[PDB]
Amino acid sequence: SHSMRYFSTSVSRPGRGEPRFIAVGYVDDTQFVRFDSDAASQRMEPRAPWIEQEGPEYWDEETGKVKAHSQTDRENLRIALRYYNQSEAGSHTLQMMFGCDVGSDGRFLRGYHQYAYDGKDYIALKEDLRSWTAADMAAQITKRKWEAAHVAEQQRAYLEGTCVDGLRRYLENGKETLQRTDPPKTHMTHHPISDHEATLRCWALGFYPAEITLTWQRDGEDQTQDTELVETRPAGDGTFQKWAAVVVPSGEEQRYTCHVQHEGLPKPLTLRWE
Amino acid sequence: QYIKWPWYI
Amino acid sequence: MIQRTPKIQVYSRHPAENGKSNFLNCYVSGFHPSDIEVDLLKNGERIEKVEHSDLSFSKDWSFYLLYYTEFTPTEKDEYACRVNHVTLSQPKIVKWDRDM
């Protein structure tokens, strides 16, 4: 089960100048491409090794498409500004995300196409890929106009086609990064904060993909009420980190177990302190 | 690969 | 507008080992809008030439970035991460801890 995803972000800058446009492309948890309008290159750039031996034609096409989207969203910021009747002194944000999910057989699962203005949902293609979901009165203006240009059928063909074609091509080219699963390297730490209580911390480093599950148990009974968990976070090398800590009364340290679930493990881990 | 979406809102 | 306050984490790429080179990470996530000031500190002074990931965001539209530099943790030097946003009334500083 793999996914490809594109994230674009347009931000108006009145008082500083023309808007800024940023777009990144991800296959699963790995970025492989970027475009910054403020950057000097004015080209779509690679961010993964396995995307570089696409041709000059590819990079030409992709540059054209992302610069086009860029210009389009610059105009959409203006149209929104009069939709919502807002001043031109304000700095506003128009985000767009789209992409597709393919199954284990290499075939279509989900399609995504989504807009947001200033952090709130605007209009979003529904899973059935035949209709839109307008989130307010202005988005309904957009919904009706698009429903009269059969835009959703145009996006279907991309999502069910082009996107899955690219994603699968990519998956094969980055087969040795995208399709391998690094298991977490796990260790446990002991941290006395008293002579009665002590902090026990379960680590998970160097894993990929990012979906992980760290749990603490006391005598088989979960301890989610006394557990401190941190968000999964990028290590910076393409792998992710996470830890879960619990405070234990001195002497009861062995009754505690740390429980790890990842794709790259044959079966779960149970960790005990010694 | 990227989308060819030119639609105004 | 739905402004979102940034969640901040400061950590090292690898388990810290005194005198050994490593990378200092500052992960700001779950914030909105995108404009944000992230600096890495070494004894209070901001580190120069810190890099950051490309601006991406989540399914709930909130942004995230990773700031980082080469750094060699000693046992006496303090490292931190100073973040200032529009939702924050004054800068937030979070200290690095090799076990957190």
Image (spheres, coloured by chain):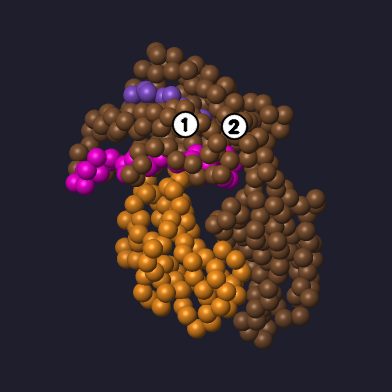
SS state under label 1: helix
Residue A98, labelled with which disc? none
Inspect the image, locate mark 1, and give the three-letter code of the amino acid beneath it: Pro
- Viewer-nearest residue: C5 or C94: C94
Query: Does residue A68 show up?
Result: yes
Inspect the image, locate mark 2, and give the three-letter code of the amino acid beneath it: Leu
Residue C31 pos. (x, y %): 42, 52
In the image, what residue occupies the spot 61% across and 81% down?
A: A193
Q: Colour of chain C?
A: orange
Above or below residue A53? Residue B7 is above
Residue A92 pos. (x, y %): 30, 41
Q: Total of numbered circles in the picture?
A: 2
Is A19 contained in the magenta span? yes
Residue A167, labelled with which disc? 2
Residue C79 pos. (x, y %): 46, 74
Q: Colour of chain A?
A: brown
In the image, what residue occupies the spot 57% across and 56% down?
A: A237
User: Disc 1 and disc 2: Cα gap in Å?
Assistant: 19 Å
Q: Which residues are magenta?
A: A10-38
> Dot 2 surroundings within 10 Å: few (below 14), some, or many (20 or more)?
many
What chain is the purple one? Answer: B
Quadrant in the picture for the N terminus of chain A: top right
